[PDB]
Amino acid sequence: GGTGPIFIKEVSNADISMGDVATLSVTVIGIPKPKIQWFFNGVLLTPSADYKFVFDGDDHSLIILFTKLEDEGEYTSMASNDYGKTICSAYLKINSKGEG
């Protein structure tokens, strides 16, 4: 009676103006309830002042509080439980201005 995680809503690509808040969202189900983790260009993200991990029911979001140009890239959500793991990926583009 246990099931590996299923993404009901996979992460979507996003375009965000530098300095604004960016949020990436998935909807996930599984038994046991799946743990959700996030990666940026292949590296697992850990707790930080720069982003928040939030959940509501089955919905999970990664919130990037004040986007920098360097936040542009490929983000991967991973759902994990005792019976499996699943990953979905999207690209966050940061529309920046400046010198350099």
Image (cartoon, rainbow, N blue to C red):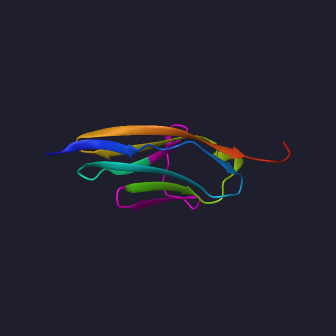
Q: Which residues are magenta?
A: 38-58
Query: Extreme left residue here?
Result: 1
Q: Residue at x 32, y 42 (%)?
A: 6
Q: How many marks?
A: 0
Q: Is residue 9 above or below residue 19?
A: above
In this view of the protein, which residue sits in the foreground, 14 or 96? 14
Q: Which x, y percent locates residue 48?
A: 54, 59
Q: Residue at x 44, y 38 (%)?
A: 88
Residue under the image location 66 percent in, 54 percent down? 67
Image quarter in which the C terminus is found? top right
Magenta stretch: includes residue 48? yes
Q: Position of residue 18 (x, y in %)?
A: 72, 52
Q: Most extreme residue toward the right, as rendered? A: 99
Residue occupying image coordinates x 35% and y 49% = 28
- Give the image location of residue 20, x and y in percent: 68, 58
Query: Residue 75 location in percent, x, y?
Result: 53, 42
In the picture provided, is 74 more to the left or to the right than 32? right
Tell me where residue 2 sits by quadrant. Answer: top left
Residue 15 versus residue 85: which sits nearer the camera?
A: 15
Indicate whether residue 40 is drawn in magenta.
Answer: yes
